[PDB]
Length: 293
Ligand SMILES: [Cl-]
Ligand SMILES: [Cl-]
Ligand SMILES: [Cl-]
Image 1 (cartoon, helix red, strand yellow):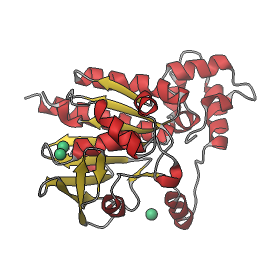
Image 2: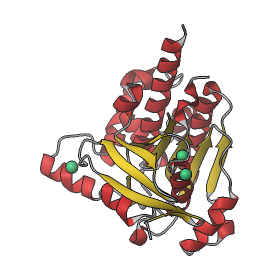
Image 3: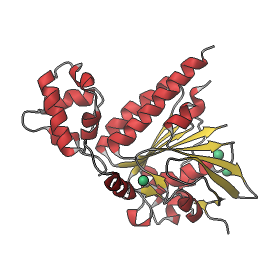
């Protein structure tokens, strides 16, 4: 578990009925309750101002909300799960792999390995922590109708998983428009509180554009917040592709992809608040992302 069950707040007066309203308002985790703005709670038909306090205080008991030393914070970060990309080179570039808790943006032109990396991740997020996995399910939001379950079979076997189980562990959803894409997230909160997910994939967030450009950006920004909110509330890793700034601001780790020779691909760290601006070379294989021969 990478988040505190909201049911743990049903004490000292908090009822199942109270939590029921919280869930209904979209809070399915203690962290969610802990990170919710007081105003949001108060505007919930049924929650008293004195009750909101009860909730906040209780949640704050289960979820850290105070100060700690930068030294301590460093330690905690070093404990974050980093999902393996399947490539030693790439994992090294990312200081271990895809960092859970924030958004990693995969950008570049079509056929640069972005989608392939997502297919691999959809599987490695399911494997044992001991081997760079997240022992959790994957929420896969596809806006281009390019996801292909069959590609995951070969990948699962490569990691010793039973293909049937691997495909069963991926909650797939095709989004047809921005409002739909955003609507899918609300349902994801519910699912994630019912089964352990370790990763959310959105290929690609830029579909958000298909005079009113300002409206597009405002929608894109709202979607990215929702994604980061889910990362905070459930402690999962989030990867988003971007076919080719709201993205530079929202994304934590931004990786640029270019096509290399043959099945080889290049990946450069474009933005990161802690990773050095370096680049590596990885490859694409019938059984997922790996390192060059
Ligand atoms: Cl750090
Ligand atoms: Cl490719
Ligand atoms: Cl790609």
